[PDB]
Amino acid sequence: KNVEPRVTPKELLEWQTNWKKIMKRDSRIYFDITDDVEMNTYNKSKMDKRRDLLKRGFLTLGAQITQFFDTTVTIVITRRSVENIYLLKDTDILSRAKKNYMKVWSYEKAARFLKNLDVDLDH
Image 1 (tube, rainbow, N blue to C red):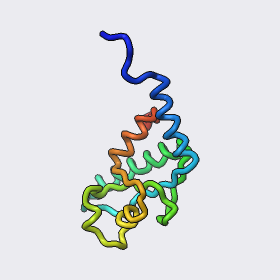
Image 2 (image 1 turned 30 degrees about the horizontal axis):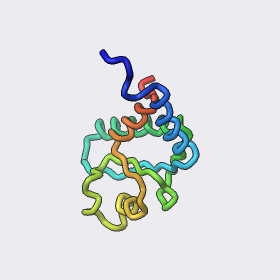
Image 3 (image 1 turned 120 degrees about the vertical axis):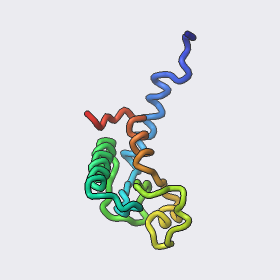
């Protein structure tokens, strides 16, 4: 009903394109392999498929996925809680990630992110 959009196609494309760079040039991503829930095999396997899907998604962006966690990581993606890292062992990669000011995402956050960049996973 009003003729000017809040955000513009190009304005949005700008936001994407900038994130897309960060991804291609600087993003080193670790998928946390520790679970905080004793799911049954079925759901454990469903969560695993989603994880793989995200990996391919980010691969599509030219990000690096390390099988191995260290200080070079920039974003950790996990299925555990993100709000309670403080309760964990200093030893824990989520603790460490926080200690090194790394970015920590849920599977939900990651999915949103990818869709916000027009990566279609269902294909």
